[PDB]
Image (cartoon, helix red, strand yellow):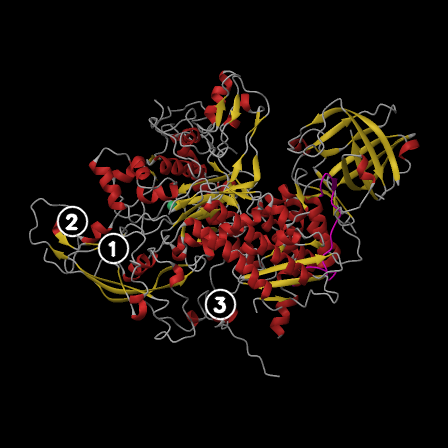
Amino acid sequence: VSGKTLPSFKPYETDAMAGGYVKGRFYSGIKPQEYYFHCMAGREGLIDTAVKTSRSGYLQRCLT
Amino acid sequence: MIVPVRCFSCGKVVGDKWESYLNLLQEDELDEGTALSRLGLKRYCCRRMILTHVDLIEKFLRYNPLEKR
Amino acid sequence: EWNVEKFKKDFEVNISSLDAREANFDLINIDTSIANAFRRIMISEVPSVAAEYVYFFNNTSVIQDEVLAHRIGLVPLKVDPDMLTWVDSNLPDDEKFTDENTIVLSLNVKCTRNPDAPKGSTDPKELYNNAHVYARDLKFEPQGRQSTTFADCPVVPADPDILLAKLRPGQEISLKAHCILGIGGDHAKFSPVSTASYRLLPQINILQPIKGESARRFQKCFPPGVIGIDEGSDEAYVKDARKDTVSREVLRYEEFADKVKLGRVRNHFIFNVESAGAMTPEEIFFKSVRILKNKAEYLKNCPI
Amino acid sequence: NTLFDDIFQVSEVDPGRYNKVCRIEAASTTQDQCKLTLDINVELFPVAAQDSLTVTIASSLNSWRPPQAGDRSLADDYDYVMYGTAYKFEEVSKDLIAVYYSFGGLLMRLEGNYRNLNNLKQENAYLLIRR
Amino acid sequence: RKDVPKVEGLKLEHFATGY
Amino acid sequence: SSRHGQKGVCSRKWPTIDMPFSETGIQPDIIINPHAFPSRMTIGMFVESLAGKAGALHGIAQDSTPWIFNEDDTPADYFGEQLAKAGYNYHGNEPMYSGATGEELRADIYVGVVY
Amino acid sequence: VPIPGVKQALEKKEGLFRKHMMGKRVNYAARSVISPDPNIETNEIGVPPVFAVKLTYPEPVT
Amino acid sequence: TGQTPIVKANLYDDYGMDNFPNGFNAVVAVISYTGYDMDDAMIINKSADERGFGYGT
Amino acid sequence: ENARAEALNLANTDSQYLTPTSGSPVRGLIQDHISAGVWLTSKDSFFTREQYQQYIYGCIRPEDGHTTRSKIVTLPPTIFKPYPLWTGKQIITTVLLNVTPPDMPGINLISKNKIKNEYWGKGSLENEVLFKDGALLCGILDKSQYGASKYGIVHSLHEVYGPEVAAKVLSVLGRLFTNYITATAFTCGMDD
Amino acid sequence: EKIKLLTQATSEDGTSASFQIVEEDHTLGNALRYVIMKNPDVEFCGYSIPHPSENLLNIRIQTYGETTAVDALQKGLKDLMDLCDVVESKFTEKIKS
Ligand SMILES: [Zn+2]
């Protein structure tokens, strides 16, 4: 709500790295801010997959 | 918990070396690599076996069910 | 055409080093098939002796009984395997154990606290009596006719200093382990070699001359005794190829990315056999050859 | 029996992420339009640019058996001999055809007129190369 | 930020078999 | 399971005579596939292999706290220098021979020690 | 806490129709972890010895 | 039988987790050689397994 | 016997090569056999008489019914001088020739794979595969020709000899790329 | 017993046959295949392990005629014995020296 994307980034920052755009690569490692953003995205993916596993069950059983 | 008789990867006996390794490390300022070199272990499969033994049997023995404490 | 004579004319052995424990010889102009066959027969099918069927009377030690049985069966025994024969399966287990194929290793120990225990003494070598059980404690005892056969042989572990179990006062171990013949392919405790492997002789094809300081660094890429500088003409030549371990540090430098090729001769193996203490590596290789020969012979003479 | 024969002048040799084999960019010095493009493993028949090579295609060398004592064939007169089956006869233009020969992958394309390429068919055909 | 400290005084460990 | 989420059931107790071996004369006790890495994208496993080999060779211990490196001091380079100083390959590759065919493999195999 | 009634005994997923008529536990059926084996034909499966001495099939003698 | 990790974090010693070793330092070969490990499987050494690799009760 | 014959003819894993979702293939080797194919069917790979024959026998084993001629058949070596060499594409060709029933034309197939020409270098034509009379002549085998991809060699073997022969081709290639990958192993590391 | 050729692939002239061997693996299969391939009379060789967990080995030798896979296998085994003998004799001589 303060406009910060993270504690380190300044409020309302015009910057790709602030806006979740990570410039690192897995070969030379990712900085902690990018690590936090990537953890957020990976967890979101896991939650979406967990929901999508059961979303189609009722549809398929009702059709069949 | 106690030093294994034979190295897993190869078979070179490292179980007659734990006390020798501890003595070499404590009596002198011998680094672990030097001690493992002097102890007959030159391949890393043997070297890690004595570099990375915990010897938890010491903590295990301090609970004797046949001795007043 | 390949013939036995055309192979005997070219095959050769160069025993570079020897010892009662570790050999390092060369097999030259032999096929990788046969060299690998020797290596695998050596590491698996060469018989040896180690305790298999333990008997436990008491074990109050911290070490689990099966863990101690595994540690005891692991330890090598300075026994020539040819002194005792093979054990049976269909025979009754009360009668399968003879005096010609079984070795009994008792181990009776009782840790007791030292009454003259010094103050400030942390090292357990003073506070307890027989706290540590070493493989030296495994004491061979003859059975039946073993007295007049194994008299000169002092049956001891090939290492008497391997640690078996650490005790505490009151705790006791009392066991008898029966030793028999076995092979490595059955269980890894019968493998008579700590290692047995080869490596083809590295080849360093220098295509363009390396002169000046360039040869000075080109030498530093390889182990110190592989490349040398010629006395008169400052250049690089391959001094001793065997001394080289193929690390390809040259290939990381572009100035040598086209002046050298790291090939490898395909018929020149460098064996390195380390006995586990039971026998000697020259005899290990000898029995590996004999096992391969007897195996081929048994296949040949076995009726079809 | 022979089906084709010539001598060729190499122009370009392309490594192309291939430790052994290479592609031959050639321009024959007899015909104004006879061209070759063959892949060979230079670990057996090494070739460099602006070098001269001989090419001959034979319907036979007189099932397969390795060479034995007292055997002769057309291969004795050349260095590199390869087996391949023609698979794609092409019609380029007037008095101009192309033939594609793949020798277990090592595709060879031959360009020129049918005044010389006529005897080539779509069947098994040996290839032979000499300096 | 100074780089990771280097473990100095490192010698050659791997010698070919027989050496 | 490795410490990087590379779980997997043991599929066969491969006999040591059939295991691949290297010039030094060691069969690795754990064989894992390389194809687990592209989709899973764990360079941590590779660098742990490198650091483990380097540490066991030099007798020392390797720290692995995140973000101690940068994009100018790659851990690959660091453990490669520590392997080159020990005599092994800078890229961690150990030239192995197949324990069945006896022939040397096509290219040097990535080996190391991991927890 | 309220005791199940007859309607509640066959109503829902854990009722009677779905839990005991559409899908039932069955005899002569095993289960175990799977492992790979590239040395069996693609229309085959690796049966452990312990199942092979337990699963059976009544063959009328002829 | 447990082993200390060579590749340990700095906090493996601040919290003192050497008292409960959860594993061992295994020689891992990133190699496609046997065919018995493609999707997610892995292969142990039979000899190493027979020398006490990962044993437990 | 009713259920035995049911599972053996209507539900057995060979009779379900494709799925009725869209009629696309669902079976085929997956990762390491594919990456080994990119190497054995590479143009740069040759194999001597012994290595070729060993690969073919280990893949086939006529004593287990993988053949059709009651005796293993062979192919002419690509190279005759200085010494007889073969090619990986010839290995695939003879594998097909040994599994495919006799007196039946081989699969004259034209398709492509997942590998662009410019990766192999200038003048390369490996993007397309040119099968003929039961012989592979251009391009390389890939995931696109065995796995989760359509219009491949195994798909056409299915389309031409039913699903049974395609199943046996899957099995035989599984035993071929396996025994091969033991000899020339596949790895990855920091250098890659 | 230990060695029995399979009638399913044997031929009446005997020039082609397949052998199934117990308690063997590459350690003998590869060496025997090499030695048999050294015979210029035979065309096909190579060995296959049916299933690793079973101690079995298969050797198939297709000759060019006038001989048998039986006698080709015998010749290969005898050549293996002689090769081991020359290795042993050279090793013993170099031990003496
Ligand atoms: Zn070791």
Mark 2 is surrounded, within 10 Å at the Cα level, by few (under 14), some (14 to 19) or many (20 or more) other residues, namely: some
Which residue is at the far bottom? G62
Please state which amino acid type lies under the numbered disc 2.
Answer: Pro
Is residue E1 inside the magenta stretch? no
Marks 3/2 in contact by CB < 8 Å: the verdict is no
Q: Name the residue under label 1.
A: C136
Label 3 sits on a secondary structure element that is: helix
Q: Which of marks 1 and 3 is in front?
A: 1
Marks 1/3 in contact by CB < 8 Å: the verdict is no
Q: Which of marks 1 and 2 is in front?
A: 1
Residue C202 picture location, percent across and down: 52, 35
Residue A12 figure quarter? top left
Label 2 sits on a secondary structure element that is: helix
Q: Residue at x 66, y 61 (%)?
A: I15
The chain ID associated with circle 1 is: C
Ligand 1 rendered quadrant: top left
Q: Mark 2 points at which residue?
A: C124
Q: Earlier in the sequence, mark 1 or mark 2?
A: 2
Q: Name the residue under label 3.
A: G49
Q: In this view, does D129 lie above or below F11?
A: above
Residue G45 figure quarter? bottom right
Q: Which mark is residue D24?
A: none
Which residue is at the far front? J97
Residue D8 picture location, percent across and down: 81, 27
Is residue I71 inside the magenta stretch? yes
